[PDB]
Image 1 (cartoon, one colour):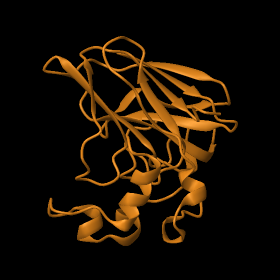
Image 2 (image 1 turned 90 degrees about the vertical axis):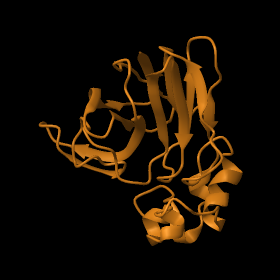
Image 3 (image 1 turned 180 degrees about the horizontal axis):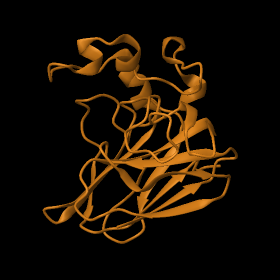
Length: 207
């Protein structure tokens, strides 16, 4: 499957694509404002994620640091990124279907639209000003709005036992972005697409 990753933000982001134990395609790239990066993701990939990283420095070997979404200091991510990260999540070719979502379970850094470019399903978006409205206790100094599990490390926020309810903090994310996951047991906002669909991920879609 093809994913076209587009930075419509006025600022540079460093896109990342991983399935947690391996890079997808090259794993990461700088995207200046307006730039597009097309990657190929192998059919059957389960548990892939795409995210943006902000305020990065990398040396000529591809090592450095980002203030949001850092994946172990690498430009080309093999692992998932440090919160806060708005996440585009997908599993492809699962018994003939693709499944996609946006998640705020690991916080929010950059607004995002995640849409198919082929027929048969709808896209999802989270584009509200979550960082500007972020509760004081969740604000990340490096930028972004952390989830409550990252900040407080309780079984209720992290859903450690598989039982948890919505919280004041999850409701904050859900009010601003109803079509993204706000906690682990949120009513699913997953979209089912035909197997082998193609997609576009757009950062700052309303910019």
